[PDB]
Image (tube, coloured by chain):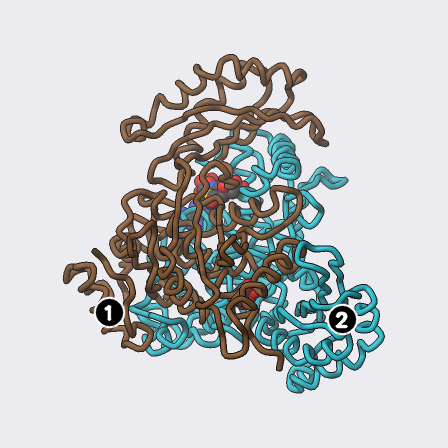
Chain colours: A brown, B cyan
Amino acid sequence: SLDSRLPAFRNLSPAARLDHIGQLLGLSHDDVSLLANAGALPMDIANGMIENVIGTFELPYAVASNFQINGRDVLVPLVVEEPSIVAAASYMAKLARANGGFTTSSSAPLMHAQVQIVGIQDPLNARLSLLRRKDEIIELANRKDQLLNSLGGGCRDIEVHTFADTPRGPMLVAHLIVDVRDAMGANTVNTMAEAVAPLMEAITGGQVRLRILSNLADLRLARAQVRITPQQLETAEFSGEAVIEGILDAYAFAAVDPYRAATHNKGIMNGIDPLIVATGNDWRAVEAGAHAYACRSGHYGSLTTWEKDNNGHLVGTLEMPMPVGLVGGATKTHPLAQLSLRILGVKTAQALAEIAVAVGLAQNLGAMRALATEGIQ
Amino acid sequence: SLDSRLPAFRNLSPAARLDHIGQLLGLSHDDVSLLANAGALPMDIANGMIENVIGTFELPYAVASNFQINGRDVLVPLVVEEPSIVAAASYMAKLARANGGFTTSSSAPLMHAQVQIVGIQDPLNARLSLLRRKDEIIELANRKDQLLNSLGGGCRDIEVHTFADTPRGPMLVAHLIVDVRDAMGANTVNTMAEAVAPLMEAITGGQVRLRILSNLADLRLARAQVRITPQQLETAEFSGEAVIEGILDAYAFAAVDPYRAATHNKGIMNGIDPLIVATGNDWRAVEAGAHAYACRSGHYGSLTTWEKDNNGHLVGTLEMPMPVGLVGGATKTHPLAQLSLRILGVKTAQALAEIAVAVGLAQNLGAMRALATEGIQ
Ligand SMILES: CC(C)(COP(=O)(O)OP(=O)(O)OC[C@H]1O[C@@H](n2cnc3c(N)ncnc32)[C@H](O)[C@@H]1OP(=O)(O)O)[C@@H](O)C(=O)NCCC(=O)NCCS[C@@H](O)C[C@@](C)(O)CC(=O)O
Ligand SMILES: C[C@](O)(CC(=O)O)CC(O)O
């Protein structure tokens, strides 16, 4: 159906760009008019969104072209201040289309709720007392949020970890594992963590302290793949084969050197965070999950991978935590976050997460390609 | 002197808040008009900032109250979508004022430019060749930006790192260490890395690949301290002494468990990134430097520290990379970034960096204090 190629888009006026988007999507007049004039976020909404509001602050709102996800073309809205990002994403997506576009998958939308318990004399024994009573705790967690349960989410499981060696004594930390459906999940799981805390306290005999989600959302992973052939990467100076080898050298550099990995992953987030902003979502949560995950091994490394396959084609992956929502907060109340969701066509939060990692992978590829092909001056 | 306490700000309308800010600072009618009306970022500017622009996207623009930095009251603009951030930062700043406010310092604005060298069988020897000729390399770097040197910046040093055994062969990586004065520094140091590459090839006999800044800006540190007394933290349910103990428990939990540290550090960036956005700065760069620094030890831990001093008072620190500019990127392009810098009063980029880490420290304190008393919900 949709054709995201957007021929000539980069050279069109903003008004003509918006008209072409509107035709492809069948946008209503009200939708297009959200960009007829500045001020689409009414001040009454802005004033209800955060505290001490005195006005609004604009960033450019753009659409990356050419993206295709599991064979379906998609248009990607992005909000950011920095040049080259949107063009690089668009151009790498153009190259990806020739080899099948981006292929994506994701896990269920599972989030951790931590419950921290201090002052237990026998924490290792208390862990087993909690695990034996897992079903009772899960049932309690699922008591209140009737809507979530009806929609196919809810607390699925508990894990319990112990930290024997802290300067503040031993700590037991229970994790509720919660399917949050189309929410990012923080209010859902924080509510459950506060709800089960008295019962955990009764089972363990400790004092509950923190009841709080984890932003290291490593059970809520999204995955993207891309493939590029050497003919597509040939430049005036370098064969495509040589460019592929240069990109592999750049990847190996990021995998060994944290000073490079930080910059390399920053480029991924140049692609991802503007889509988070465009959909009214929390970009600090996505950033923290991204970079903490990059150093889960004890070494801060690259979130993407880059290889050559047995045909000599460049293949990239991005697998990372990606907690986002279609509901909640500004995603619902900002008229342009709703328009962004309309432009994307996503029907679940995990579908939005899959587009996010495709854009992050495309952005990293574009950044590496530029650096690997620039002549010595 | 300016008074940042902003009486009843929480309950004034956006218009009345803006009028009061304008009166405190002596803003002109035309400056106040930039926030009183939508559209301060005109489309010809937005269309020139990034590619494929179709419009602009607003976030609320707020001011946190009560902040005081090295004895001087400071108004802090913040652009973000999530509720309770601005309120919690203002609340914690209120408490800090009673004990001297926030005390800050920072290093010189030093940034790394990486120059990756491949193609030689003797990287360990080539590193010494580069160090032997380091003055010649530094002089060439500095010939490329005479204005920066006159402004008191420039390349100060080089350091060279080797990776003799990678899966892609031997590499060595030179770092130019560059004082970038009031810029974030990326374009400034990339230019120097390009300029020295041919000399580094001549010295080493190798091939230069990547020439690029590092976002792990660990020579560009900003520092903040805060102190809170137990009487300030007493609640109806908890003695202030008990709250202090509970905050130390929360800190120890972040220091041992990355699932908590990621969330703890996310709470810091809730305060920092909105100031970065409000000043037209690159928040992906600040995020990447923050989270990579947090795992420099081989364990992803807390950016802040929390302790109790000899008087029983709670004392907090935040020391972290903080690469921001007053010039460069979009700092000058966005009329409201310029207005933010006027509201802040900052005259150097390191002064902005110091305010950023004070806000981050305040934000973390606010999150932990709520989690250690009634809970975040
Ligand atoms: C502040 C609260 C939201 C409510 O305050 P309250 O009711 O207790 O006391 P109050 O006597 O009424 O007000 C005390 C002072 O607060 C300011 N103030 C109060 N309300 C105001 C308002 N509406 N407008 C303006 N200024 C207001 C104002 O300065 C006021 O002073 P005032 O006397 O008026 O001159 C508090 O619950 C509090 O901090 N909660 C913590 C919230 C928090 O951290 N959010 C972070 C985001 S979540 C997540 O992304 C991060 C994380 C948690 O996961 C991170 C992690 O896990 O680590
Ligand atoms: C090219 C960039 O530095 C990413 C990278 O180096 O891979 C990102 C840009 O914002 O500077």
Crowd class of label 1 (few under 14; some 14 to 19; many from 20; radius 10 Å):
few
On screen, residue B346 versus residue A17, left or right, reads: right
Secondary structure of the residue carrying tag 2 is strand
In the picture of the structure, the residue carrying the numbered disc 1 is A37
* Local secondary structure at mark 1: loop
Report the chain holding disc 1: A
Q: Are marks 2 and 1 on the same chain?
A: no
Give x and y (percent) for residue A244: 54, 64
- Amino acid type indicated by mark 1: Asn
One can see residue B194 in this view: yes
Alpha carbons under labels 2 and 1: distance apart: 51 Å
Disc 2 versus disc 1: nearer the observer: 2
Q: Quadrant of residue A64?
A: bottom left
Image point 56% across, 75% down: which residue? Answer: A374
Q: Quadrant of residue A122?
A: top right
Location of the N terminus of chain B by quadrant is bottom right
Residue wearing tag 2: B158
Q: In x, y percent, where is residue B32?
A: 38, 72
Q: Amino acid at mark 2?
A: Ile
Please say if B345 is above or below A162: below
| Residue B355 locus on image (x, y percent) | 58, 61
Figure check: A373 above or below A290: below
Looking at the image, residue A333 sits to the left or right of residue A271; the answer is left
